[PDB]
Amino acid sequence: AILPKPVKMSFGLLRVFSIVIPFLYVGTLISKNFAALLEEHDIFVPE
Amino acid sequence: DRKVMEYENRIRAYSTPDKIFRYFATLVFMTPEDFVRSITPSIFYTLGECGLISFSDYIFLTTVLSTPQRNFEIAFKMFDLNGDGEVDMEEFEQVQSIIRSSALTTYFFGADLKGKLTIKNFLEFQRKLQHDVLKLEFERHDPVDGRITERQFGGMLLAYSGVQSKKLTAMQRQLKKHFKEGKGLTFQEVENFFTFLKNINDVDTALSFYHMAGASLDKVTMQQVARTVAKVELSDHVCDVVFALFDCDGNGELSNKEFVSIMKQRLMR
């Protein structure tokens, strides 16, 4: 016999994209914020 | 061998001067060259060998290196017990036993143990000693015909400030790229500017007058106060170097906590 249907989920591509993109924006935001936060003190290292 | 370098920096910047004495002495006594190695990360032939017996000549010559002029005159006031205006080496021995609790004493007071010392000789002593130290610091960096580079002068300023800043270190190594040409810094510019930096507590008066209103420091005000309290002339190239080195936020003009508060705190300790 043959197995049943491989089950999918409720619009997986859309919810994966809709959770990966705003948290990517939150990541780049807090990266800029941390860069400024220790650019204020002398802990940074760009040269 | 950068570890011994930075370890000697950590010793010389913060430790008690007796540990600095026992660290930079070989004989327990120092030569004047031992003293120069203690103070750096011809009066040598006048200082002799009988010097820094119990690390108290160290404290005294440190005081000579670190005393503004009115403070220098009131130090001469607190030397003189009877207040005759003269301090022989005998009165200095009487003060010096209290300090602790001789070649320079024979040299500058009297060879026959007879000191008849005016204010002017004491002033000459300060000027010769500090000017020889400043000339040694100007010539350690090998000036290009009496003209040091911008990073050399910035390193001298950061060595005088004594604060381990890495923001200002990055600004120092950027200075050659900021001022893409550098004509050099003459010894008279260095002389006048460290003469100005010697007296910042006196300079702090009109600065705080200006400052508790507002922290907006331009160069014409600094040159007026420099020519006022020290009669020195700050060339505008030196002002360009100071503004390019210390203005961290880059707003054009300095605050207290950018430059003056740090230099004052160095003058405290």
Image (cartoon, coloured by chain):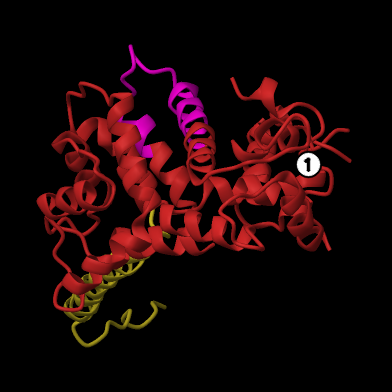
Residue B11 image position (x, y, % from top left): 68, 50
x and y percent of residue B185 in the render?
28, 26
Image quadrant containing the N terminus of chain B: top right
B110 lies above or below A3: above
Chain seen in red: B
**Furthest residue toward bottom:** A10
Neighbour tally class for label 1: few under 14, some 14-19, many 20 plus, Cα within 10 Å: many
Nearest to the observer: residue A31 or residue B255: B255
Q: Which chain is yellow?
A: A
User: Which amino acid is tagged 1?
Assistant: Leu
Residue at image position (74%, 58%) is B95
In the orientation shown, which residue stands out farthest toward the top? B145
* B137 magenta-colored: yes
SS label for mark 1: loop
Q: Is residue B150 visible?
A: yes
Please determine whether, in this image, residue A44 is positioned above or below residue B143. Answer: below
Kindly identify which residue carries mark 1.
B52
The chain identifier of the residue carrying mark 1 reads: B
Residue situated in front as seen by the camera: B74 or B27: B74
Dominant secondary-structure state across the stretch colored magenta: helix
Across and down, in percent, residue B48 comes to 75, 26
Front-most of A15 and B34?
A: B34
> Which residue corresponds to the image point at 24% horizontal and 43% vertical from the top-left?
B231
x then y, percent, for residue B113: 78, 37
Q: Residue at x 54, y 42 (%)?
A: B122
What's the magenta region? B130-154
